Image (spheres, coloured by chain):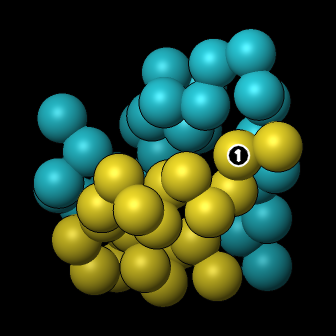
Chain colours: A yellow, B cyan
Amino acid sequence: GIVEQCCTSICSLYQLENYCG
Amino acid sequence: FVNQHLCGSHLVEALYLVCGERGFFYTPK
């Protein structure tokens, strides 16, 4: 999930946009 | 500003700024 990709590891714009509506 | 560790409310703030009018879903699981 997003916490594993963006909080416990370094986030990216690609990963954030995966969660946009 | 997105290429760092983003936790808690800082992650939700990043989604808000990046996604804009598209909205987003936050699922910490």
Task: State the image quarter where residue A2 is shown.
Answer: bottom right
Would residue A2 appear left or right of A5 to someone viewing this image? right
Element marked by disc 1:
loop
Left or right of B12 in this view: A6: left
Residue B13, placed above or below residue B21: below
Image height of A15 relative to B23, above or below: below
User: Residue A4: x percent and y percent?
Assistant: 48, 83
Tell me: residue A13, above or below residue B19.
Answer: below
Q: Does residue B13 appear anywhere in the picture?
A: no
Closer to the camera, B24 or A3? B24
Q: Which residue in the structure is indicated by mark 1? A: A20
Classify residue A3 as left or right of residue B4.
Answer: right
The answer to whether residue B4 is seen in the rendering is yes
Name which residue lies at 55% across and 52% down. A17
Q: Position of residue B5 (x, y in %)?
A: 24, 60
Quarter occupied by the N terminus of chain A? bottom right
A7 with respect to A21 (left or right): left
Instruction: Please give the chain letter of the residue carrying mark 1.
Output: A
Amino acid beneath label 1: Cys
